């Protein structure tokens, strides 16, 4: 019973997901039949299960091919703890059973995030897309608590959780929407619109990830980091340069990936949620989070923020609504900080964005009451000309870039602050 | 530039039939046109012949490239002795002429299976698929003898015998079914169903041959063989491990090949006979042989067993039907053992399966008699609960695995008897 | 490391330099033409392809001109939109002049910098000479009110048109926009594709065969012989004059046919540059055939406006004197547009005096023909000999003008430069 | 001038026609618009000229790039001497003017064939496909003499004489048939049939030229030539082997080229004359020349043989028809040998085939009169069965292979000279 299985895995091809442009040749041909079927309102179940698995495995057979075994564990784990809840949801419905099942479904993510904190080495049950997979898994469990979801076969569950395009780090979806958009193949005109948008997304992804992302990440970021470290100190102008360059590099690389993922999803007939919709023209933090990482932000708003507000109002822990809203903002953003990894700078990012949202809500209330004061006194309301818009965009852009510097992790390198 | 023809043949590319997964890329592309042409009612004869010859030659080259010549001679031999009988078939059917023609059709296989035993290593005319091509040749001399075949062209004959997806060691076929199947191209929906089933077969063959066959073949079997040899003796627990692991490895590897062959055959518009339909769950040995290697077992039942029973009843040599059935069982299984190869363990395998079949038949007769005895005595008949079925399945599974241990030739290493 | 050296590292593809460039262009522009067949336009794909090929054409040995292109784009956007906001209110007849001057300012700086110190200014790049003409066009089309509303997409799609850009035919905004909006039907698209293939073939013949023969086989040795023999005039001077004239035509017409072909592959029929110029009977009929786009641009926006301005102030006594002065000034402005050297200005003034002499000769011929018809004498016949004489004299004068424009007289002589 | 243009012509890209399988990717992508336009009943006159000129130039820009200049002369020659007849044909029809114009049109071929005899070096006017273009450019004059041809534009003349596929060494056509097939674009069903036949021809051309021609020409022919030269003498077994191998190599290489040319022609909507139609089952010399090099043989039969027979019968030079037929056979085959080139072995080939045809006609007459003699005497007519047909096949095959040995020029090496 020799254990050379790991070395067997570290031999397969390693076609990187959305790596070289030539990838979109292979994938394109691999997606040529499926799309054709949609034109005849015919869906090939087995062929999709073949292409999705082949490309997932090709994406996961890298230097750390062992993660495949972890994946083959993870899936099984979810099948154990989703279906279990379904059985329970047929008969009884208690808060503590739902909480336990949510915790047990999200436990692999908790282990992957916490193990480096304790051991210092990556956990065994960690693979490429786990952070963006439990979101689907636990998502389904939440839908069973509300009663929205009642029946689903294993084929639907596994084709939803393991969606090929949005697997590595892609838009976070929901089961209800994905299933409803999977059942009803769009008519020919909508399918043609989807094909045109997919080609446009592929071209823009080429531009974003292979040109602008490369310029901002492999040409300016390393020398800027080196100069900032060499000058040293608490802060310096090269740190401002690296902050802005990293913000733009992060945005362009992630937008390129998201455009690729949405294009490949459209080629399969499913419209995955968008990720970025002009995030930098946002003139406010609350308007920013409706532009930046749309899928993740909306997921945390629907399932972690709204539910917490409902829980807090159920027990009326806080008297006024504003205090409860601020507390929910802080807790939601802190949980979003943990999700990235339990280090010092991710928690700082979460607390910083939570404080930003609370400050923005307070300023909205103060602006409203100041407008009331000026209107009652007969004076004109506060200006809303181009200058106020420019000031708001400038403040939002600066705060967002500060957040992307803190999230960058460069603040460890600049000053070795352990905690 | 050439030297000897054998060296030039060795220089040619070698593609193991269903070896690395990339093989299915080649075939896929090579079968991309033909299958599309199947949707309409047209077939590309030249393209099919060229691709079939290409892949047969690629599978035949390598270290044993000289066998290609052994193929060509073989083909001519069949064309000499099939067509000859055709002419004779139009005049009269004398039994001895039919026997002579069948013998001369199977003569290359007789030489291949009898040459290494006498003094040599391998006969010259031996090549890769001769074991599973004689069945497609002597399957015509019989069909003419019964008159179900009267007219056919050389194109049909050499397109049926040299079927590319079923050449090396594949599902044995019959001429009448194959020809009548290739004449009538299926409809559009049937073709889509066949494509979906072909993709399912490809995936399941991947699992059966590149994972499970690898696990049971090169991970457990060599260490278990080493432990069994080191412990020595008549038998040991490592020998039992070898038995079970080799049986599962044989089933998984062969079912992987057979699913690959059925998939590639479906991609060319022909549904080749299925080899395995859930073995290891057979209650009886008689039910086992309707599930394990279905194509060959059915071939021997139709053309070796039933004909033997008909011959024995024609001369009424034996007193009753039961004796004829038992003798036919023994002789048919001995002929199967001979077909595998003239060694002590193959003949032991054939005799073992024959004794199993006759004992199963005797047990069925005795059970029917005792059920009649209980019915006439008023007692409730013998139980048929889940426990009895489980016991029957367990007994059949153990007997089959013992037969596969004998067929493995491992007992030759473990005992060195009859060396 | 990212510097100007990074820009210089980028691949370089001289526009219409080798046939493989046309293979690249055909492969790139096939989807656009196929989409045009179905009356649909791929806005993002066209922009990406145009930017790609502009960058490839600009990333030469001196690839530091891309920064100049970006600065020029920003400058033109700023001033065009500054006028657009201002035009809707009122036109002061001097703010229009200021905006036109500030739109031609990069070009005038580029054409005046090498004269002053030693070299061209920083903001010089490849197509700046044939891009200003587009920008000023818009300003003109705002002063007369024929243009009122347009978006930044239309403006930057018209100005940075990839097929022409470098030296291609000069377009106008009104015609270009009305042509871009209305995709032609399928039969006209097929006719345009066939004409594009014909243009590609004829451009091959003109630029890669005839231009090579007249520029690499005869011109260098003829120049060497002319320099060796020396003197004001010589037979090698005639050789270099004729060879350079034919080289200029067979190279520029080849480039313009390439540009029209590539433009037709994107659904727009750019103005034709040459319509068989060497058969022009008169000097005035030569400019309707030689560099048609530029000559028509100067006639419409520099000549006619100058005549209208002079007439509305009635500075001169009669119409013919105004026409002569407008001819001379327009051709001098054309020479200046080419570059501030002695021979370019000599070329401009030469063409101006040629046009005015042609006009005077036509008027004198009309008067003398009227007198002869009054006297009963038959007018001078023109069947094959007079027309041949006119064609020959116009061809000789044009070839002399191209000798002057060549700058070869700068090498042959050493006049004050 | 400088005169370096030839060196310029040598730096152009080179692409041997039908040299590599990758060449057909370029050819198919270039010819796709023409085929689509055919499907819509449209011909793009300019685009066809562009693709034809580009591929002619790519075929002619080899080490002998200077031949392009010769080609540019050849066209300018032929035009001058085609229209010089077209103007004359309308006015007067003296025989000697037609003879003079035909001679002047064929003069470049005469110079290319004669100058190596005198000077010993290839002539300036020689280029790749002059021998298969003079045929078209003299066929137009021959048609014009008969009055079959009338007003024709220069576009038709130059698109006929310079056909892109059948240019280097391709099927020899006629103007009337080519023009009539150019005007009437086939229907959609005929276009589909042409596409199928073009793909079949391309595949068979791959097989014939890149596999079988390579086997017979680059692996067996050099060793057989070396052995035959080493043994020496008038005749030897290696020389017989080289005779048969060269015959098969010539047939396979030429048939591969002809299938390629017919395929590319079908992709343009024009079906050029076939070149080979089962040559080796001829059973006779006449049935061979009606099967071997169909285009060239039919051209020489229509314009050089029939015309000479008509001339001889016009002046009744010989007493009987058989003598005139034999003389015409000999003269036609001598002119064919001359067309191949003025050496000893080409003229020997021509006179050998002429004698073969004459004795075949004598054999037919003698067989007919012997059959008449036997019928008059009441005896059974001479047999015509499998054995007689096999004897005829054997005799014709041996004579044809001897002819291809003489045409090979190998007899010049082995027999004459020294080595
Ligand atoms: C009434 C009495 C007089 C009648 C005369 C009838 C015949 C007159 C024919 C005169 C025109 C012949 C034009 C071509 C002759 C030479 C062609 C030849 O030999 O073939 C060369 C080219 O190959 C061809 O033959 C190409 C095909 C053309 C065949 C002839 C076409 C014209 C036929 C016209 C027949 C007209 C009959 C009368 C009609 C009323 C091969 O090159 P070479 O180097 O071997 O040339 C020969 C060598 O130099 C010895 O001089
Ligand atoms: C369902 C139909 C379609 C299925 C997919 C069809 C396409 C499949 C392509 C598989 C091969 C991809 O080919 C790709 O080649 C690249 C570049 O050479 C190689 O690249 C890889 O090499 C090895 C793994 O082999 C890794 O250590 C390396 O880091 C990685 O770059 C791999 O060999 C393979 O990742
Ligand atoms: C230390 C923690 C981080 C500090 C974070 C600082 C960022 C705080 C939020 C950004 C500043 C918001 O401050 C100001 O808000 C007002 C009031 O909505 C915005 O004003 C706008 O608000 C909304 C748009 O969403 C509209 O309804 C309104 O009409 C418009 O005026 C201004 O554009 C912005 O300048
Ligand atoms: C490496 C092994 C090489 C051995 C194989 C050699 C290739 C096999 C040769 C096939 C024989 C070719 O000869 C064949 O003759 C038969 C007899 O009519 C005809 O064959 C035809 O048979 C039937 C008749 O309807 C058709 O359905 C079929 O599609 C067609 O092939 C053709 O004429 C020709 O295809
Ligand atoms: C030494 C080599 C030989 C060893 C193997 C011998 C054969 C192995 C099987 C022996 C019998 C086991 O089979 C056991 O009995 C019979 C045989 O069909 C089955 O039962 C059978 O008999 C009765 C009716 O006749 C019904 O129950 C049923 O319709 C039928 O299948 C049992 O459900 C099965 O459990
Ligand atoms: C979405 C885009 C679709 C458009 C299709 C793709 C167009 C862009 C890719 C083409 C890039 C060509 O890339 C360029 O090719 C030229 C062609 O000689 C070569 O260029 C190199 O050699 C040439 C001449 O030999 C020199 O003049 C040049 O300075 C040097 O860089 C290089 O290979 C590369 O610089
Ligand atoms: C090499 C240097 C290149 C410099 C940059 C060149 C590109 C500059 C940006 C081009 C786009 C600017 O145009 C801005 O974008 C949007 C989104 O497309 C345009 O939107 C629209 O533009 C035009 C206007 O009808 C439409 O034809 C087009 O289909 C649509 O995109 C807006 O009109 C404008 O707000
Ligand atoms: C740089 C110095 C100037 C260079 C030369 C510039 C002038 C060159 C052209 C001068 C001649 C004008 O060219 C002249 O054009 C007119 C009108 O088009 C033609 O035709 C005219 O004259 C002919 C003479 O029979 C008559 O038909 C009629 O009077 C009129 O049509 C003349 O045949 C041609 O000679
Ligand atoms: C509308 C017209 C469409 C035209 C389609 C495209 C035509 C152009 C084809 C590509 C240009 C020629 O591409 C050709 O490629 C071959 C590939 O060996 C190379 O050419 C080669 O020719 C010969 C044999 O082939 C070699 O011995 C030689 O060393 C090399 O020059 C060059 O790279 C180029 O001559
Ligand atoms: C230097 C001379 C080179 C030429 C060499 C000979 C070339 C071959 C031509 C000779 C004829 C061969 O082809 C000949 O055809 C005739 C009539 O068709 C047939 O002739 C034969 O069969 C016929 C029946 O048909 C019988 O009368 C008899 O057995 C015999 O004459 C044979 O098929 C073959 O003998």
Image (tube, coloured by chain):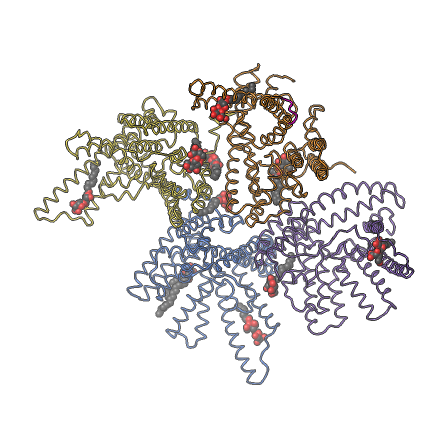
Chain colours: A orange, B purple, C yellow, D blue
Q: Is residue B269 left or right of residue D339?
A: right
> Is residue A315 on the magenta stretch?
yes
Residue farthest toward the left in the current orientation of the protein: C375
Residue farthest toward the top in the current orientation of the protein: A233
Q: Between residue A301 and residue C354, name the one nearer to us.
A: A301
Q: Is residue B336 left or right of residue A358?
A: right
Magenta segment's dominant SS is loop
Residue A128 shows in the view = no
Quadrant in the picture for the N terminus of chain D: top left
Establish if D51 lies above or below B176: above
Percent coordinates x, y for residue B94 in the rendering: 75, 72
> Is residue C273 on the magenta stretch?
no
Establish if A49 lies above or below A255: below
Establish if A117 lies above or below B110: above
Quadrant in the picture for the C terminus of chain D: bottom right
Q: Is residue C223 left or right of residue B409?
A: left
Q: Quadrant of ligand 8?
A: top left
Image: magenta residue range: A314-318
Q: Between residue C119 and residue C328, name the one nearer to us.
A: C328
Q: Is residue A240 left or right of residue D156?
A: right
Percent coordinates x, y for residue C145 in the rendering: 30, 34
Where residue B369 sits, quadrant-wise, is bottom right
Q: Between residue C2 and residue C71, name the one nearer to us.
A: C71
Question: How many numbered callouts?
Answer: 0
Residue farthest toward the right in the current orientation of the protein: B377
Residue B144 shows in the view = yes
Percent coordinates x, y for residue B383 in the rendering: 86, 53
Residue farthest toward the bottom in the current orientation of the protein: D377
Where residue B50 sits, quadrant-wise, is bottom right
Q: Between residue C187 and residue B383, name the one nearer to us.
A: B383
Percent coordinates x, y for residue C243 in the rendering: 31, 39
């Amino acid at each position: 019973f020799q254990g050379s299985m790991i070395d067997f895995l570290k031999q397969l091809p390693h076609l990187e997901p959305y790596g070289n442009p030539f990838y979109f040749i292979y994938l394109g041909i691999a997606l040529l039949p499926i799309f054709i079927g949609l034109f005849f309102k015919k869906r090939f179940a087995i062929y999709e299960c073949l292409v999705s698995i082949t490309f997932i495995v090709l994406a996961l057979t890298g230097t750390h091919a062992s993660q495949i075994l972890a994946l083959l564990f993870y899936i099984v784990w979810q099948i154990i703890w989703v279906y279990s809840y379904k059985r329970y949801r047929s008969q009884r419905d208690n808060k503590w059973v739902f909480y336990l099942h949510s915790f047990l479904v999200v436990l692999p993510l908790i282990l992957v995030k916490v193990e480096p904190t304790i051991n210092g080495t990556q956990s065994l049950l960690n693979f490429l897309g786990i952070s963006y997979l439990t979101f689907r898994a636990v998502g389904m469990i939440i839908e069973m608590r509300d009663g929205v979801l009642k029946e689903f076969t294993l084929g639907e569950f596994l084709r939803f959780m393991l969606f090929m395009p949005t697997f590595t780090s892609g838009p976070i979806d929901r089961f209800k929407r994905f299933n409803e958009d999977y059942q009803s193949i769009p008519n020919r005109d909508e399918l043609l619109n989807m094909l045109e948008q997919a080609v446009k997304y592929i071209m823009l992804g080429f531009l974003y990830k292979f040109v602008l992302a490369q310029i901002f990440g492999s040409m300016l970021l390393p020398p800027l980091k080196a100069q900032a470290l060499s000058q040293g100190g608490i802060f310096n102008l090269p740190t401002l340069g690296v902050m802005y360059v990293y913000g733009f590099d992060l945005f362009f690389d992630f937008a390129g990936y998201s455009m690729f993922a949405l294009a490949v999803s459209n080629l399969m007939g499913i419209k995955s949620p968008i990720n970025f919709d002009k995030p930098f023209i946002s003139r406010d933090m609350k308007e920013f989070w409706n532009r930046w990482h749309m899928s993740l932000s909306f997921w945390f708003r629907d399932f972690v923020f709204m539910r917490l507000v409902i829980v807090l109002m159920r027990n009326k822990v806080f008297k006024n609504r504003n205090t409860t809203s601020n507390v929910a903002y802080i807790i939601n953003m802190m949980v979003m900080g943990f999700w990235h990894g339990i280090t010092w700078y991710y928690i700082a990012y979460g607390i910083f964005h939570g404080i930003g949202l609370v400050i923005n809500d307070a300023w909205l209330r103060k602006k409203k009451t100041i407008n009331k004061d000026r209107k009652k006194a007969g004076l004109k309301p506060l200006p809303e000309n181009k200058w106020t818009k420019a000031l708001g965009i400038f403040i939002t852009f600066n705060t967002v870039m500060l957040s992307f510097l803190i999230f960058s992790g460069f603040l460890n390198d600049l000053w070795f602050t352990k905690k």
